[PDB]
Image (cartoon, rainbow, N blue to C red; front, side, top):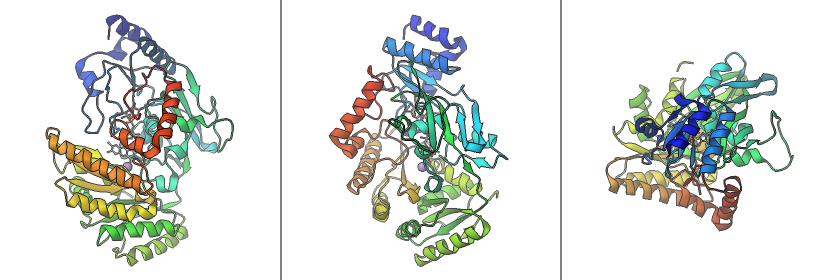
Length: 455
Ligand SMILES: Cc1cc2nc3c(=O)[nH]c(=O)nc-3n(C[C@H](O)[C@H](O)[C@H](O)COP(=O)(O)OP(=O)(O)OC[C@H]3O[C@@H](n4cnc5c(N)ncnc54)[C@H](O)[C@@H]3O)c2cc1C
Ligand SMILES: [Mn+2]
């Protein structure tokens, strides 16, 4: 980057909000994944959407790649600057606006996290349910198409994003569903909002998201249930879904993950394949769901439910499973798989994955949003041992391909980033790939919007 270009950036955002210092760039060259740190040439913090537009147009017309950066909690290398360029950290735009409690909607800027939003909504009777374990940017969650433990009942980001404000790569401002609009359904034209959810910063910069809010549950009950085997836990899961019990959360932990979480969080659950469950409803609604769910789990060998206000501890431990797995081998990094399959095929692939981790020299813990047919294999890697890194990559690719063989997808929520680009080509085939590329090319003709990712 030339000093003329750096001074032009400073003219837009202000001298304090541009940095070419190596330490600042290195901090913005990686996320939480094992993908090697690739530092951008500069980091820029725009203060309002006009500045985002002017930064993008400056980069775009000068041939400088743009990397949108939220909270850097992604796990597929989305923020790695594989071709250099300007990292745009969006978190100084941190305001909540247009809170419309009577319409169940709110507008947030990229610096707002889910925790910040739900704190703002305390005593409103409303909450935002999509819950990645990390304290992530909500606009980042829109960009990756995130989900979480609550998705089985309340939907993913795709279900709960109503509208997006997007700075296109050349600086034009798009409101995907129209400026200020919010509604429950529309057939007006082509649905542009869904194109930008899950685009990972390769189609434009999300500068605000309009989110669907939900009523807080009348009553809540949480529980854990220990099983004799992985098969018994996943069969119970499938049978619960096929019986249409509207569970609020249904999370699976294998024995390795249960032990890891015990050690990391001062939980002390029996070390066994375990379901964490949560139910929402009225008093009698809960009782009926509990009875039907306990009957199914018992038939598969489940323990009596170990019940859980502050006992928040349960789900905080789950949300930190990524770090619990890391702590099994301090100094390691982690790679996660993220397949999602037709639910009737979930038992076969989860059991086969357990058998394959056991038969291998890798350390892996299994944790999953199994109510969606989705699970994570969290594989640890020595950042220095390459033989291991190649064994971890090969394991993840084989798992991905088995999921594709079953009619599923290689990622339910984390995205493609750098890691799953070949699997995506296998998943949608040549006409799917060319169609996605044609969309990328019309929005980003010069290929400068987070290059090297997804496609
Ligand atoms: C402990 C832990 C638990 C997690 N649990 C979950 C989980 O349950 N579910 C889940 O889905 N994910 C989960 N994640 C992954 C991560 O939190 C999500 O993918 C999240 O959506 C990333 O948001 P971010 O702003 O931190 O992303 P970043 O790493 O900053 O960016 C991710 C990608 O999105 C792009 N991007 C970011 N912000 C924008 C923007 N405003 N406009 C356009 N593009 C943008 C970036 O360029 C990059 O390609 C977890 C991560 C951790 C560390
Ligand atoms: Mn997850």
